[PDB]
Length: 118
Length: 118
Length: 111
Length: 111
Image 1 (cartoon, rainbow over the protein chains, first blue to last red):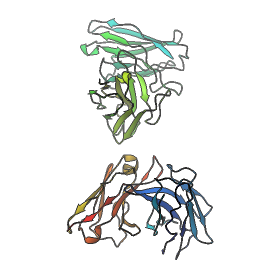
Image 2: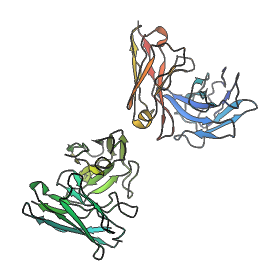
Image 3: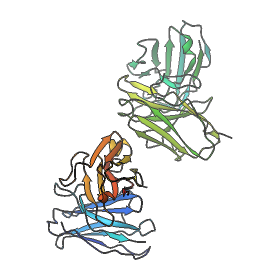
Image 4: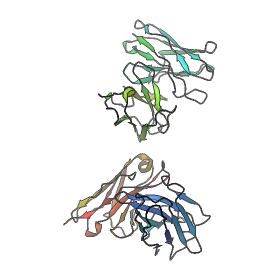
């Protein structure tokens, strides 16, 4: 699992969020990449999970519908966009293959991550 | 839902206490009063729970008898009789409507109360 | 005497948040929700928090309650003049097959 | 801000055993297993303990986890210079119906 992720981005508050997570060396149709952010000093913070097949997704109860997670099987990528952009958003966004059992359940291998400063 | 209980009762120890609370502006058949013991400035204590239909009732786990239930649907009234009075019986009777669900269980409201001195 | 162990008395100034804890057993608290009752002195008791997650009749949302294991805690953030009341825990018990009740905790308003 | 609470930073001498705590309620700790992740400073997090008992082969025996009711303790043990990392306790939460994580503890290697 090479785990490809986009670079660090600082577009400022009220702008946009871009987080592409590319699968590599594995089958993406059975491997998803759920998203976790780290608030400084607050540890890991769950934001959502994706299903490459069908297209179903689950978002954090705290987060609104503004967070948008989708998957592209042809390019084997997971696309995450957050409409909200505030000072609290500043975090490093990490997406991980979800373990095993067709890989939708619980985090094992996080990628390099994308530090977003807002 | 307004419940009207009897007034202050003073009774000699070892005697019998008759106390009733009335149903007003409601379906007495579909309402039940589960009597609750209440010592002044002290924790509540369940006595019994009855139903107007058939007349089935359940009493305190500690006391197999002690208190007898009766219910009259025509007068929409519930009567409680206590026997073998003791000094510990100086407390209040609060009745109680039974929340929802055809009003056979749980507690929602209470009658003004009936203070008894033994 | 009460199965549910409540403190006998408590104090609190207006405006602050205070918790009251009642503990019971796993058959009545760990297997059933607890119900918190409030009772102004000299008056009939009312219901403050029920099902641990809702208020029966639009009761001030500043009131709250939590349940964990065999323990429950009522937290109120917004102390006010007529908050002096007796607070009770109630829960069904399968071993006794009846509603077991707490010993009642008096919340007062300090000067 | 996280639901699960962890110490901010626990330090110990090399060779010594260090305990990291994770406290919560029975909804996520009592009802669901506790797991411990570690991330080295500047590196992606790697699994340390999952389901409180099994480890992913490479992990040495020093790292162990214990769960008691609503509390969890990870005894890292055998402190080495590379122990310095952020430690996060994680569990499924039924109230939130999702993964929840701890506040994170910064292990420090003393001289």
